[PDB]
Image 1: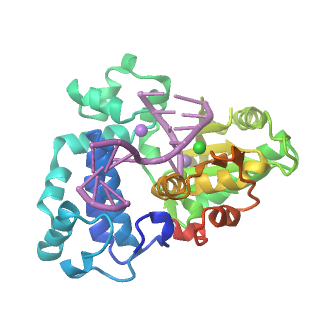
Image 2: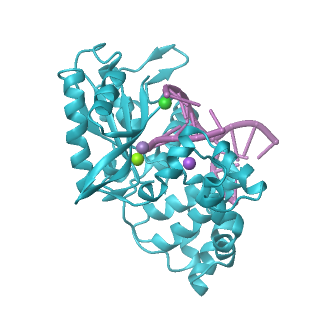
Length: 325
DNA sequence: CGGCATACG
DNA sequence: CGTAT
DNA sequence: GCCG
Ligand SMILES: [Cl-]
Ligand SMILES: [Mg+2]
Ligand SMILES: [Mn+2]
Ligand code: NA
């Protein structure tokens, strides 16, 4: 089992679901406390289990696996022996975990904002509503739409949204294309947001495109909220006899950069962190959603496909469906 | 022990 | 500070 | 929290 998640296939569904979910509770809790190192190790240990070909049934099967030390192994040991891990259950029950989770789920609220509200004594969404002078307009949107945004987006919803986005993109710039990215491109059947990547086959034609797209969507009455290359929107999506608010992210890239942006926006988030870490630490190349830089030659790698990029980095190619780290 | 991904709004 | 993967 |  290699040590980096980008070095191994990770399917969407797997054989250690319970064990990985427990570790990911501890990762999330570490994040709420500002401990990014411990978050990362628990995330990585969870991801290793997702990559295994069968269920872990005994503690000895952890021997030799990367990212499994005293703490993560103990978590698994307790789950194997008793069906529950006391530490994990304590986190789950805690007022701190539950409130930080509730608050950071709001669009516009991060760990630092959640933490300050927690420390001021706030606990509930209605606590926040009763003091709206304390909220940004982004947070106000996030709070008004919180119920709808908490309901999973389905793949049927995605196809309807894609047709709508293509229509506006087509008026804004004939020939521009719309590609589904994010978790749905990895094969997820549900999600909490839809991600699209927009480009045009003629380099440079995409300059200034996103404002033109947003103006057109707004004119069609589709935009409940938005604030450039990236747009984080709340869309009005048709429902039987009504509609619901859906988070949609729109990203534009020049076609020269499209493979990098496609790779970068298709995720998973842990997969991208591990791939960038691998690039820099193992190959000495600097990766982002724009390009891949050799800091010795001071040159950028030209890529025509995601396949090109995996080959550049000396990694076996992984389709999106195997990037669910 | 240092490091932990890398951007844009 | 927030957002994204 | 774990790797190297
Ligand atoms: Cl980036
Ligand atoms: Mg997404
Ligand atoms: Mn998104
Ligand atoms: Na949030």
